[PDB]
Length: 33
Length: 49
Length: 49
Image (cartoon, rainbow over all chains, first blue to last red; front, side):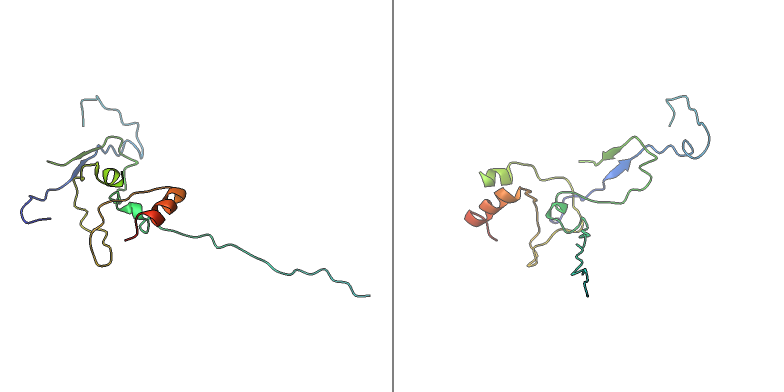
């Protein structure tokens, strides 16, 4: 990395529905997150 | 009378255990532990370029 | 043909934060995976660093 260059961060947006798994027939409307 | 059937040797091959960061093609990617991706179907990697 | 193969691409967007060096310590920017048949005839007549 040369001086400057604005080193940035790589963000991982990841939809985690837990408790979907586990127990419960979790049911959602959709248009929900 | 003396007769004997003999076992003259036993040979085994050692299965080579190789890890993935030896290879030259680890230059080609970034390996990171991400547990819970079983849980999540959706994926997005966003970098502001 | 190699230098075209070797350079037709765009460098990625990443800074691994640990880079493959060459033991003098120049960084490795590429991979170049081949078949051993081609690799052979390639290494003897062409590339040996």
